[PDB]
Image 1 (cartoon, rainbow over the protein chains, first blue to last red):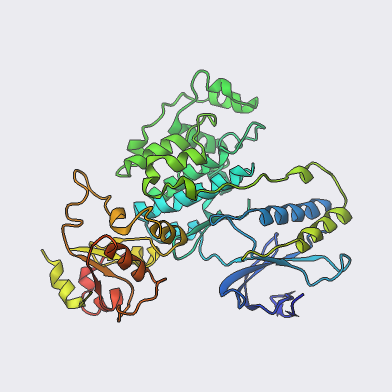
Image 2: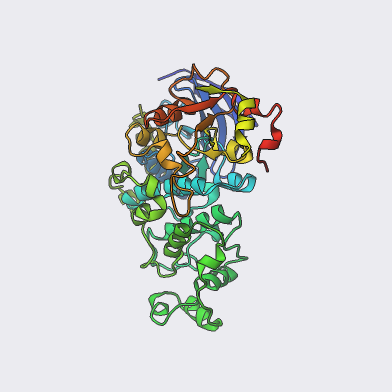
Length: 334
Length: 130
């Protein structure tokens, strides 16, 4: 065990190991408080998240459990990774505080896009990276479900990481109105929306309340086919579309004027309404748009992820301890 | 090896210029005609230290009929933010990575002394902006 040093930042008290220094309150929210720091034992500016009240409920206890397990699992250059996790508590009884440490990743795709206009190579490199970790994440049989610019962290070297799994603007149609027939391919719709933004600086489907969200979408890809329509769910959902005036699919070449041809072809493959026709991360990696960067040997996959615990229903005591277990069985990276 | 901000100015009006500063800095402003190169990040360095790809190879994708003319059909200038004494440049610095990769392809590059920061003393009219 190291040596912690207490201190008080913005009405919350931070107790952290000697190695983390220069804590600077970057913000907070429901999830918890986060301080920007400097890890003398690594040279990295880092982000320390103080998780408080992680066990003030079953829903919360489990949630805290989930995030931690999930975070301990991902080990990929393009996915948020846990540099450290600790607790000043010494006994499972004095335990009720969790601190997560990760590379302080400056900026986010949102900030970047709103600041400057990127070159095609930038867009290409950024999206290559999203796809690379998306391939990894999907390997472990995990769906992100909330992929959006604000969830994409980018440093000065244009390296990107995907973070913790308006949101409606990037949600895929299937999981849009709430249908129990979604899958990994739901994240590709998002990447398509994102790529479109990178390429034009304009939100593709800025819908007001998701009714029009579907209208806006349909307005581009076109109203369903004959069988395609018979490939869906819901009662309402089904009717609305027929309740709409049949619109024809636009030719992306006219929507994304002056854009790289291989780009619009890729979008053509991601922004497909039939999730079963939608290209995979792996398949997208190989598209001609990523030629210079595609290296199959340099595109790792995860190991299965035990989502088993998910099923079980336990009590705060259980989940809490179960979390202490993870907090202790933690092996730093090297 | 090293060229002067002045020599480049004139050299310009009528050579390939590579900017190896951070992408956001490059997008904020670069010497007109300068082409950007991502090389410092892990993936770039890796695949470079593996021939998977090479700088000169990369920038050979901005044509329409022939992809090399005007490319290796000119001397290559290279610049960063401000490296004054190029002779001494760490192996991590982007400047180092490019130079090694180009030289590894039998190409003699020329580094602009004092990078972009210098070149802007009396050449602001030779730059793009926002």
